[PDB]
Length: 120
Length: 118
Image (cartoon, rainbow over all chains, first blue to last red; front, side, top):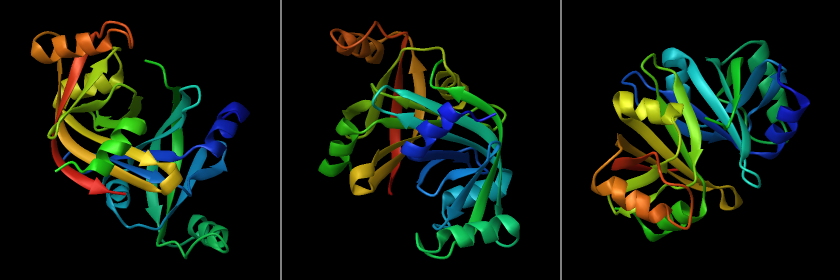
């Protein structure tokens, strides 16, 4: 689903994560740790315990954008997300953080449902 | 209000614009023409019939982010937005576009309400 073309662009750019709270206010947060779990799933390490984690638990709806500013090319990923603090996803994230950053407060997981580029 | 370092990021970084549709699905996309109209207001040139435009028209809810990857610094601007296709803001947008881009289809105006650090 997520192609090699998408992966290369992803690997270079900063993930910008958009969510929405209970009152319908959008939130944007960069997530440096965002990465592919497999070719249909994103995973990131939740280090901040901020509005992104709240919104994900609140309603799960999410979009992630990556923009290549050298050509204004990019990809956007619409999916459903959840936050977990124990279990396989969390343990993988905990393993991944060793050497890179601190122990994750939680892990965020995003199941990709639709993929757009920057057009329209 | 809007500090000089905020203006540095606004003028040098790419505006990432988050909105939401009637069903609660967030949307996000870049707007190269996003700029300070004054110390309390953003405006940008709407060149599309895209989802960002539709969402602002629907409910006016918005957040704009700017990120300097180089210094790991950023700002989030919370506000309420509207789309206009005629009038003073639109005329100003149309004038600004001359020598920069095509004639705008519309203008987006955002009243800033709160500012956050990243």
